[PDB]
Length: 125
Length: 125
Ligand code: NA
Ligand code: NA
Image (tube, rainbow over all chains, first blue to last red; front, side, top):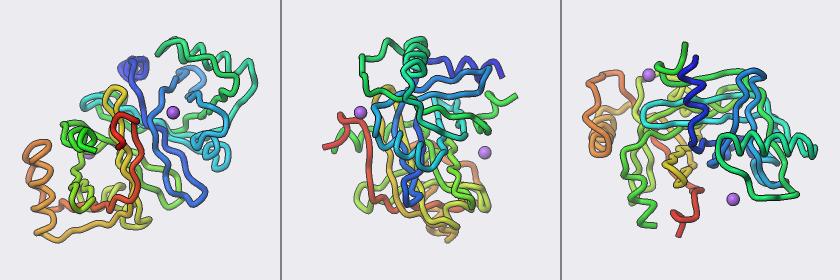
């Protein structure tokens, strides 16, 4: 829905859930971006972070955002992309929502192909 | 830390992460309470909810709260308690942070024994 898309444009952090090797959830705050056309969500991080290692190793992620009583969780399949062009593009998408990220040659992108969306009733449909 | 305890008293929702049978994370917004003395976090829900089924079946949960740049994730071992006295007590703890919950004879409590805390640097130590 359009209210959902506006919510996803607001400047807030979200929680990224990935799985550790033992299947325990690792849940940490991140910024993210969401492309409504492709359904790809992106998190930028430094290579080798626990987020990146978990996303690469287990292949899934959830991004969960809440403000007041409004919330969404976006679930999907995750991979890590270290291609320089992909990283630049993700940095610019990030800047579009947040602000210009600090330069970091070690930056990688966690790309999540969203399959399922849960959320508050005011944001679904 | 004391700033962490104050953060955990503020009236905000949080995300509860549990695992589905297939190990995919189920992440939905909840209110919760946290007892600093016992390290028990509590979520009230209607019996048979996906949260309750996942907590009972897989035995783990994470509660994650974010406001602005401040955040905490509380990880631990989860169980479902349907004892009437436990439910009343959890309802009152909930009311202490939020407001009196609607009467519901089917209410159960997800009790999470917190083992690990992650968060923003301003809240740890
Ligand atoms: Na960091
Ligand atoms: Na509900």
